[PDB]
Amino acid sequence: EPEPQMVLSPLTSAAIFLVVTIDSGGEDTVRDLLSDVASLERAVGFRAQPDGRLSCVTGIGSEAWDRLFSGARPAGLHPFRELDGPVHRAVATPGDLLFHIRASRLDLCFALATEIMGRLRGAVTPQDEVHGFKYFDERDMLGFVAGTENPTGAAARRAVLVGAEDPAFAGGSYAVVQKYLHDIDAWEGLSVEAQERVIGRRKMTDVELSDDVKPADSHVALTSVTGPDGSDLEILRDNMPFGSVGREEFGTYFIGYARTPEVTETMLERMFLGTASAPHDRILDFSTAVTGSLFFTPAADFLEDL
Amino acid sequence: EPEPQMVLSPLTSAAIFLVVTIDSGGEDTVRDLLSDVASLERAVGFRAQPDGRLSCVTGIGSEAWDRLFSGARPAGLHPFRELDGPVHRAVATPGDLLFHIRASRLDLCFALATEIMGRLRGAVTPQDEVHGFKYFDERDMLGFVAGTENPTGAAARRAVLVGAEDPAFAGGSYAVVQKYLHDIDAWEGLSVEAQERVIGRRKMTDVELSDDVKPADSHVALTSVTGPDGSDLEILRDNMPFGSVGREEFGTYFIGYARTPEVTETMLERMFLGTASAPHDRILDFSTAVTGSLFFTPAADFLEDL
Amino acid sequence: PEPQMVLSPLTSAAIFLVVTIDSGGEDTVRDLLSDVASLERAVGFRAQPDGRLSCVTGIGSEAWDRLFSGARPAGLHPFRELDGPVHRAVATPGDLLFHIRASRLDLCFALATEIMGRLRGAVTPQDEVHGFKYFDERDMLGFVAGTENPTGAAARRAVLVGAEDPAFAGGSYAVVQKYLHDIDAWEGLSVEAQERVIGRRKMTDVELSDDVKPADSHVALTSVTGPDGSDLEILRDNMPFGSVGREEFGTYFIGYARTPEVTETMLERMFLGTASAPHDRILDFSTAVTGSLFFTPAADFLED
Amino acid sequence: EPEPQMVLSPLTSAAIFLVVTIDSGGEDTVRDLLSDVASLERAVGFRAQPDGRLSCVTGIGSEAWDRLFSGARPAGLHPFRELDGPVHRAVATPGDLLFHIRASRLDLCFALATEIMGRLRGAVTPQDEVHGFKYFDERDMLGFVAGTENPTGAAARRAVLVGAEDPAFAGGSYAVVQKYLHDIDAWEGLSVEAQERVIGRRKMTDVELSDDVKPADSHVALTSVTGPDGSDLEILRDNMPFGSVGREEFGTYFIGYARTPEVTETMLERMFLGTASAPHDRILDFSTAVTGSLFFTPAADFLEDLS
Amino acid sequence: EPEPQMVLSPLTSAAIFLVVTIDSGGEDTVRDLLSDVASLERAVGFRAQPDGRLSCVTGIGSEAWDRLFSGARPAGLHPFRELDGPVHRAVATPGDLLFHIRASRLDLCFALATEIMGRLRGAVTPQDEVHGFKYFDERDMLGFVAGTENPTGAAARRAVLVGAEDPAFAGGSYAVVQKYLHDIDAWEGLSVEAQERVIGRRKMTDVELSDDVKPADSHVALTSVTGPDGSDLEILRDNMPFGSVGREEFGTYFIGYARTPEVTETMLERMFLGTASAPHDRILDFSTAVTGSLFFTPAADFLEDL
Amino acid sequence: EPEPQMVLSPLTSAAIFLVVTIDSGGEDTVRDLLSDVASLERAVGFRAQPDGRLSCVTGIGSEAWDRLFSGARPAGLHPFRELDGPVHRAVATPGDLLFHIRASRLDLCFALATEIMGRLRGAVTPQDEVHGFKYFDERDMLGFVAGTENPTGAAARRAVLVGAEDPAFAGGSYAVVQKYLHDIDAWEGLSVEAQERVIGRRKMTDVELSDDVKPADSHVALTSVTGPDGSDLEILRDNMPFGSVGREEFGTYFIGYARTPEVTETMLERMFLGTASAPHDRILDFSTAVTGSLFFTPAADFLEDL
Ligand code: HEM
Ligand code: HEM
Ligand code: HEM
Ligand code: HEM
Ligand SMILES: [Mg+2]
Ligand SMILES: [Mg+2]
Ligand SMILES: [Mg+2]
Ligand SMILES: [O]
Ligand SMILES: [O]
Ligand SMILES: [O]
Ligand SMILES: [O]
Ligand SMILES: [O]
Ligand SMILES: [O]
């Protein structure tokens, strides 16, 4: 059986998201780090157990894949597709490696990020570094409970992990990242009732709006997708608030894991391009994407045997 | 008896330090915020009891004091004194207001900082914003336990709180801040034994080096000071690690509270200018001050009664 | 097939809600059943992961016929009243059971509020009990309660419907009885006399050896061996409850099993006695004031 | 410095409020129990240290005081004063003894309530019993954070504990209890902003409404009282949610401690009878008081030195 | 004004009791260690703040006091008084220094005991070392709750701390230690009701037996003492269970703190020699004392100034 | 189908290791206790759910197996093999039964140990009893993190549990125990860099030394073993510190679970007898084995069905 990376792990109160590009001739240094990254995770995390809950998920971009490895490519791997909607745009930004670092404490994230970047100095250029913090009541930067409808157990495994459709990369997953900045002044001008119509859930109680009152351009309505079979298409999201009060930056770092990028890309199409019944997702009237990248997160044993 | 701010409260795992200057015409907006800051601390923190441990200490600079208030000035309040040592410099940087925000979680610090800065928008200019995190084993950025010789109980109250020497300001304190960036590459080039001789304590066990072994130019030696009366002069320090792995920023945010700035200033003179037996504090060969500001943190009732 | 949380452990808080379905309330009920997993997530996610909020939903025999056409679960019937020589196990009305558990009563109450809010005008409440953990997993008699519950594979085998009734695999049967205790009479016994009623040591919870365990002890009468000589097991989530002012010191009994026959055999031995035992001596200190039987379907049965 | 009961202690996650009346001839049994109540609290609580946080505050009503004790009365002790407003009524209901029991767990509350009621069986009649629970982030059944502006440290000591004004009773306090039931159907028909105008604080973030927007008939406006010298008059509230989903009971158990009942009573007069600017507290349009009792909670040493 | 050691602090889940004798010529080494013990306590304890709750109380015996110090002695400091009852004996055993180490975790106790014994190697001989542990709900090896009637708050300060009756030694206290082994076989031969008549409290619920059923020879009856003026004479007990299952050793380590040894010794006389109404404390029919030592625990500042 | 004992369970903060020999005629009493040990575990542990995490793993020695049972032996069961190296010796010491008792608290361990030994009194003779405790951030007495490279999940199950190679004993495991005492004086004389060369990892950060600097006689180098097929051969180690400060006993209690003893024995051979490039494991220059025993820990249902 192939060992997945910790893609199925739950939300934690802290995260570091590190996106880098591989400099010309940095390939060899990168391959050596990838073969050690699970051992670095154990080195930093084991002594802080059991409360630490440290994990690192490592992702590799479409272009970087061709630079690093000969042989088969994962079937779903391609650069992030820019979406030019009538009003809102999903931008594509450079990204060769993702490190999705989670723990109960920011210091354990930082210590692992320090060892990884120590090994990669002179081989990579940092593109994005975000320090995420969840609110103590599981709320995001808009004041809503975040993660409620994430799949669990066998449903999560089936939605997130590559299987027989691409057997050489079984136990892998696809990660889409987008850094969003919010217009908090505009958001806080809405009544609570208006905010609930944007999201599609009650703010205090987190109960879903019933189908007769849920607007067709609510976040929950547009990111609800049924397959040909009639079955719900699901992703696993580990979204984190981040910000700087001095710079008035109040953000959500979106990360969504799926067995194929087509599920996440369908949701993004419905959000940015809309449908017959909805011009666009009302959350984008308060949220601007400033990054967008797609990564393949291989099985742990693929990184180890390299 | 006057009610002090939470200057005596213990170290926490998260902090936000905010330093701002007051723009032209900003004084009325600032006075309104000062009269409300304790009530905002309760609004953000109460619902997160008892695990939240949210506090805010508010400080006011020498020039800002004269802009905001008529009548008496605290006896020790003056702008930070630059020290131009033969090798190392303690710089002065602008700062009218300090908010020293502590909690068990960064998101609680961030929520109070958001409310404070929301009320000050258009009246202030941000000078500095640092998000602090302690390592899970009470270690600083240099790998040493930080806080060990802080005073506690009655000795802390005597060391930190203004009393009858300045009775109109009793229950106040003086805060000096300095942001330090470390040369971690040079520090990690030392053996553990050489680092212990820089600090003056054992790294793993935190046991102080004996007087026979402890170098005259160690941090513990130079920051150990006796008054004319033979008594130890003590300050309370809430130093926090901070940084950015992508930018290679690895820092210690120094904050020290004391009943009179003369004690903190004497320690800084010994570190930066040295003594007969030591050229300077050896910690400064690995640590560059990039900010320096002095604040008076009044009694809580002083701020309430505006 | 995915079961409801019938295999989940004891928690420190619980709400037990039993209602009857009023005439014409069927459609409101079916809509709520299709939504109960989503309500559970909605309330529970506000306290992940320590909250441990779950709701197990059960349906009575008469309600089943009012709600669904086609196949019945093989073991579903109304609770069988037992009229013993001394003690009686009463059958009381109940169409729906909500077995709500969490680490905190707030999560239980918030979920109960949303469920009952959705069913207002469609159901009549019959029983509501707010259970709480009592010291080191003790009951109102001062004994540790749950010790011999099966775990892991033995729990799955004992609790979940399998191939014997394949349309309903991953279901279970719940029996509930609210008991009120005579604490005055109980505290009149020596600790040694109480140990002989239960069949375990009071402070240390060690089982009495077979040579000393009375045949009419609770542990002896509820020990049943199946055709192959293996133990027939149930999973019990008993919770203390009460009201000091009204002198109500209670045990809310709930037992899950793959077939009701196992639980019913245990109840027959307790209430009717055997050749060796007049009745379960625990009943000399405990009166059953409710009795109901429910089928707790697979989670997938409810969503569909 | 005489030793107070645990009146200054913080909110906990569980509580039992027990109100009883003393039957004729029950006085000797009650005095005996009062002399033992601190020892019973230690007997239950000590084995759950350090996390248990079990405490019991024992209060005695005006008429019970006269039956139990032959000497001096606390200066402020009198029966609860019924308030007959143009719209709303604050009823006075019987209660001789209050047990305010708090812990981090209901089991410790229940076990201590069991031991106390076991000692008083046949001497007292139960009037009210409420099992309170913390609801999410210190919320009440109206969805608002409750307790935010409670005084702390020295301010709490000054606001709550009897001192030199009544020296024989120094370290005592005065507790007012009211059981409120809420009309949740009517409450949930308001917009969140209309709820915020009833309470005077933001619902989700618990920030006080600015003075320009805070209505005069908001809860926070009517329960804000200044003394003649301009300083705030404060009380310490340990309010707890309770209820029963089947019976549609969604309750707030109000308890307020103060150094003199005059402060709590001035707040109640403003709520129920209103001011020049406000007819009544808008919170009462959604809240009905069904009990009302006043108790003196003596210093701990006063109870210990009985017979 | 004088700062007591942590004699008033509550029970913890772990303790180490270390009793040593001072070798001939060990006096100087011992004096240097005593002046450093508070600094060693902070060095170990600070890196587990705030849940560690590490503390060390240092006690000095009567014969050791006269070897270490000159001038005035604490008024009540004498060797433990052997009690030769008709049936039961309280033995006196050697001991010059007591280290009473408590924390929430054994590791912090063990690390501090290691640093102390490292400084004293070749100057002292170990007489007794006991690792204590919390047993369920504050129970002892007899199955009863132990510590229930300890004084708290002001009553504890008044019972425990030397004051104006011996002003030079204000802030000190007197510790009596006795290691007890229990005859568990004999004890378990009693019914629970017989055990309750030995102790004087209910076993499961820890409710005191009423005055009309409490035997005169029960432990609670003989250890209840009133002064000539009617007030209760109280001690503070920090008893801890210990044992070794292989050796069939089930113990109680008794430690009682009091402002004068006369209170503790009056209790011991009643237990071992009895009263007019009681031959001896029935708890002694199931408990054997194998050590007995008395120590003065000076104010913290007395040790620091050496 | 067969239910293993709790061999795969994680490290806990407390342990008791009990090794006994079966006295002549004690066989019938032992068989009765083996059939009840799981019942005793529930009796003590249930009341402390869910935080207690009490488990007992019961092991039987080679000589004991033939005294207790008729019919098939586990294929790998033999007496511990004494290793007589040029410098260091791995002694074989008597042991018929192992009880490996773990929990989050020592009380639960002690209570279960008391019930087991109460049933075995007069049938067994105790050989060793060790009370283990967690030391800071999962450290051993040498000050290094211990457990870091233990296998987890599927890799742990594959490394530890007997499968189809010995189908009658599927779900069993083999436990090797060795009690080590450390020369802390000699160890603490080494610089941290020289200690790192003994172990093969960085002391404070627990990062593995790179292959270019790791000495061939380091602990990590000698306990790293590859099968003929190139895979890593793994064991599960649940090592616990123990000690007594007055007796200068600073111990590591070694316990290693494996699907076959040949893996553990290959590691011991390399440590004690060395390789072409290493005389012996340098850790043995600071560590003396004083016990050595091998046990088969059967499937839980094997014990239940006696
Ligand atoms: C500013 C960015 C975002 C914010 C603040 C945000 C917030 C939320 C919230 C509050 C919910 C409801 C509770 C939950 O189930 O987590 C939700 C649901 C969801 N979001 Fe987002 N979201 C954002 C971006 C995205 C993006 C970019 C996607 C997909 C590409 C996405 C996919 C989903 C999905 C699939 C659900 C679950 C819908 C359901 O089936 O109920 N979100 N989000
Ligand atoms: C530049 C970055 C700094 C770092 C990384 C640092 C770190 C440390 C460490 C590790 C200790 C030993 C443990 C303890 O906290 O007692 C210490 C002690 C101390 N530091 Fe700093 N420190 C810094 C700057 C300062 C400054 C600027 C001052 C004063 C103006 C200061 C004053 C002290 C004092 C008074 C002590 C206690 C010494 C004693 O009496 O034992 N430190 N510091
Ligand atoms: C007054 C109501 C009850 C009380 C207070 C009570 C209490 C207990 C206690 C203290 C135990 C021993 C520890 C353990 O849980 O294994 C026990 C065991 C048990 N009880 Fe009950 N019980 C009650 C009613 C029932 C009922 C109504 C049934 C069955 C229909 C039942 C079935 C069992 C079973 C099967 C065991 C396990 C026996 C074994 O195999 O060891 N109980 N109960
Ligand atoms: C249905 C009954 C009640 C409910 C739901 C309720 C709820 C609240 C809420 C939500 C607050 C705002 C947060 C805070 O606690 O500071 C508050 C404040 C307060 N309440 Fe109540 N309350 C009730 C009855 C009472 C009564 C009867 C009194 C006095 C007799 C009282 C006195 C106060 C006071 C003094 C404040 C603080 C006002 C300030 O200075 O800001 N409340 N209450
Ligand atoms: Mg009978
Ligand atoms: Mg206020
Ligand atoms: Mg014996
Ligand atoms: O999301
Ligand atoms: O510092
Ligand atoms: O049960
Ligand atoms: O309130
Ligand atoms: O004691
Ligand atoms: O190891």
Image (cartoon, coloured by chain):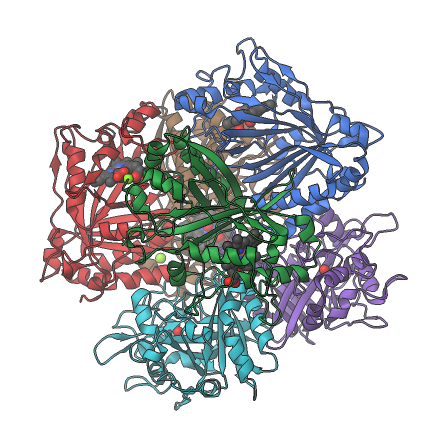
Chain colours: A blue, B green, C brown, D red, E cyan, F purple
Residue at point 41%, 21% (across, down): A190
- Residue C49 position (above or below residue B165): above
**In this rendering, position of residue E205 left or right of residue C64:** left
Q: Nearer the viewer, residue F139 or C231?
A: F139
- Residue B260 position (above or below residue A288): below
The answer to whether any part of residue B93 appears in the image is yes
**In this rendering, position of residue C285 left or right of residue A271:** left
Percent x, y of residue F229: 87, 47
- Residue D91's quadrant in the figure? top left
Q: How many marks?
A: 0
Q: Nearer the viewer, residue F181 or D66?
A: F181
- Residue A15's quadrant in the figure? top right
Percent x, y of residue E72: 38, 85
- Residue D148 position (above or below residue F22): above
Q: Residue furthest right?
A: F276
Percent x, y of residue E280: 36, 84
